[PDB]
């Protein structure tokens, strides 16, 4: 067992350059991370660099990080990403529509991504917990289940807050065993990741994955 | 009237329908240049301001990170225009610019311009807070060659906003042929006037009501 297989090696900064993407993918091969998460402009490069690393998936983000574009654009960006080599996509919900109880639009928005990814990529639904009430977190997860998503995910990392154990337990309670639960945003050390795992997370989104795995190895050394 | 140069902007991820209604009625009251809303709200803003052709509907493209593909930016532009947008603000591929990949930066801008061709103004956000002085110059030059209509300082989601020296640099590059928009950090009339005196022809802000109410 190793925590690295549950970590999405993420780098989504707007000023990210090619040399940083190359290093991220090489780190993913060395540590056997679950995936690399990069912005859609880097999907083609990540897929080429990891073409012989089948256990390391290419993940990208859709309608990210604001989630306030139309369902038609989110589906097009999903299909475009899959053509470029993405096998996982993390979409952001329409938070405003969720605030307005426009549940049919929130679900159709998620379903547009799911339909474009059908049979080709996992879809993770970022509900952006730092912006939701307790009832909205539950409603968003229920819409993700009804839409056929594979994962519910806490945070973009670009909002006010990140993953909390209480949110993860809430999300795991709604989706049960049928969908994965991803803790992202603010997961900085092994203590953070293990707390999310205990709360019910099955995938960790982080940028410090190397420091997290090295902390795991240090528990075995003198 | 400085109101005619202000883009009444509200791009928060948790923005709700009642806030867009308040945004549009404020713009139709003060005759702002435009409202700037995320693409999900374009169709609503276009109908709320159908009887105010002087107030355009502006939306944002590949916003705010600029790190999606040119084909997606073009689709989002075409989709935004179909929904009622007549001005689009796109974010450059910053990583491509920092990597000297000038053909991709220009092709990326070019994709939005061709989608908007004859239907909408294109504003190119160069995100000055992440750019060296030379990259700021190169970004404007690539905007001119691709056929954009404006150069814009900031997305409103970075660590820095418009500065007078940045506005003057961009104005010197594009001259009179393209507009210069100061966005991010402008909160009063004194800031707005400082950007305009530096060469800006459009102001992006959220406190446009407080700015115009200080024109006494």
Image: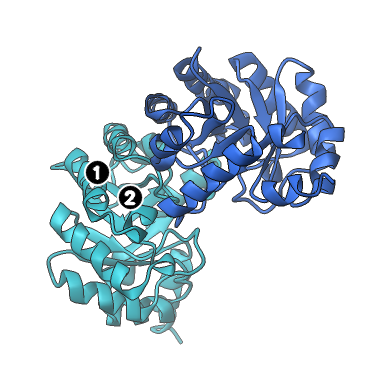
Chain colours: A cyan, B blue
Q: Is residue A169 above or below residue B27?
A: below
Left or right: where A165 falls relative to B36: left
Which quarter of the image is occupied by the N terminus of chain B? top right
Answer yes or no: do the residues labelled 1 and 2 have beta carbons within 8 Å? yes
Using the image, determine if residue A186 lies above or below residue A192: above
The mark that comes first in sequence, 1 or 2, is 2
Q: Residue at x 40, y 36 (%)?
A: A45
| Chain designation of label 2 | A
Residue A26 visible in the displayed image: no
Name the residue carrying label 2. Answer: A91
- Per the image, the residue denoted by label 1 is A113
Would residue A18 be found to the left or right of residue B140 on screen?
left
Where is residue B158 shown, x and y percent of the image?
63, 51
Name which residue lies at 74% across and 52% down.
B187
- Above or below, B130 against B16 in this view is above
Question: Residue placed farthest to the top in the image?
Answer: B118
Packing grade of label 2 (10 A; few <14, some 14-19, many >=20) is many
**x and y percent of residue A150 in the render?**
19, 57
Q: Position of residue B52 (x, y in %)?
A: 53, 29
Give the camera-side residue of A200 and B192: B192
Give the quarter of the image for residue A95. bottom left
Rendered residue at 66%/42% (across/down): B154
Dot 1: element: helix
């Amino acid at each position: 067992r190793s925590i690295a297989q549950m970590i999405d090696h993420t780098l989504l900064k707007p000023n990210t350059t090619e040399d940083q993407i190359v290093k991220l993918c090489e780190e993913a091969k060395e540590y056997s991370f679950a995936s690399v998460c990069v912005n859609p402009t880097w999907v083609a490069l990540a897929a080429q660099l990891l073409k012989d690393a089948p256990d390391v998936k290419v993940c990208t983000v859709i309608g990210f990080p604001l989630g306030a574009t139309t369902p038609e654009v989110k589906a097009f960006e999903t299909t475009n990403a899959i053509e470029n080599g993405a096998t996982e996509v993390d979409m952001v919900i329409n938070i405003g529509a969720l605030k307005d109880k426009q549940y049919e639009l929130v679900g159709r928005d998620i379903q547009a991504v799911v339909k474009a990814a059908e049979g080709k990529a996992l879809t993770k639904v970022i509900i952006e917990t730092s912006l939701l009430t307790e009832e909205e977190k539950k409603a968003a997860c229920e819409l993700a289940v009804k839409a056929g998503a594979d994962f519910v995910k806490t945070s973009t990392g670009f909002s006010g807050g990140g993953a909390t154990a209480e949110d993860i337990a809430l999300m795991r309670k709604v989706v049960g065993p049928n969908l994965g639960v991803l803790a992202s945003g603010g997961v900085r050390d092994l203590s953070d990741a293990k707390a999310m795992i205990d709360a019910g997370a099955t995938r960790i989104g982080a940028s410090a994955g190397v420091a997290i795995v090295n902390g795991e190895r240090s528990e075995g050394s003198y």
